[PDB]
Amino acid sequence: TCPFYKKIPGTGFTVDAFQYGVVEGCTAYFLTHFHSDHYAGLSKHFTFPVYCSEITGNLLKNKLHVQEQYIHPLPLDTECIVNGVKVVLLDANHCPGAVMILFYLPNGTVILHTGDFRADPSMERSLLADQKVHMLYLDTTYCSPEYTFPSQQEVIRFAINTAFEAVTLNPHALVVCGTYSIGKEKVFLAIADVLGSKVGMSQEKYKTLQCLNIPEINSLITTDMCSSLVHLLPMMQINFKGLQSHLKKCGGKYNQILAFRPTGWTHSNKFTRIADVIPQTKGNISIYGIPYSEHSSYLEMKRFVQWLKPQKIIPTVNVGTWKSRSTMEKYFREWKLEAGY
Ligand code: NI
Image (tube, rainbow, N blue to C red; front, side, top):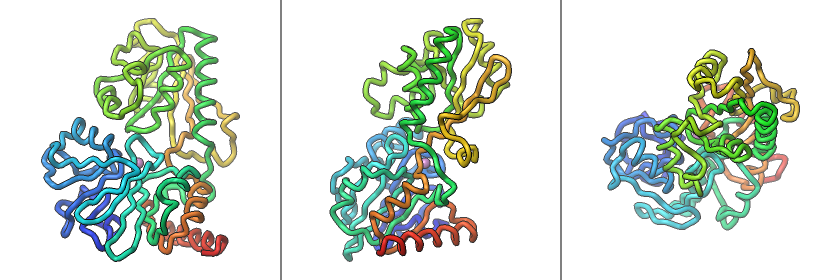
């Protein structure tokens, strides 16, 4: 049964609610982004209207085979009417095609559902600036002050400088980057660009990337592994055994691997700066865990909420334990008392 925090009161709508069967009273199913915990349940046999971004709709059609007649893509930053209710999709600064949804209820209530997001001050100048928001359905993934991480720009600077140094010292080094979902494409695209290479990958991953409207993509990626010195592999193969095995497959073209695992947060964040990050090494294989996040840090989340000043907050992440829920509610009250709303 669908939980309350996935339902939008006063409408026929649900958000990211495809694993509960036919939801009673639901006339339209919204999907914020193409990540499996959110799409879980969709397939070619789904016959209700799905509302989403253009990019999410490309992925539904091509990867899950949802039929076209049930996919309703909406443009961003544009007022649209869905089953008698005004809605707007906004960029969530998460993975490609990820959106936040603004619902303008018939009684005058305005609700923002963030989906998954990485808050940014640029959001303070979107269509959010123009009216009051009463209820916030908030991505609380990292809602505790211990969660600090660097900007995406500092992390990509580190990665580019690390890869360029290694390959210039040893032109026979291969760079490998792990992946298991869409998102974080900048990591592997920025490294391939500094090296003058395409990124090589499986046919299945190439297909997925071709759905993303990324500019000039045919110029940056390939299925010809032999021509590429940056390879993408499944995240589960980014370990010493998996990488040794890959290096064997390359036929003596390479004699060293430098590999990257983009994690979100790891407790090495509470002590060490990005500048100071070191790899795990075994023989001719080094693995770097880099803190590339597509979710808000604690401070970014706090700034957004203190700017928006909602009347009520509904967390959508970390809701399964009483300790988590109590921690989050304490921070929400602090924020409100400090800012004065
Ligand atoms: Ni996500």
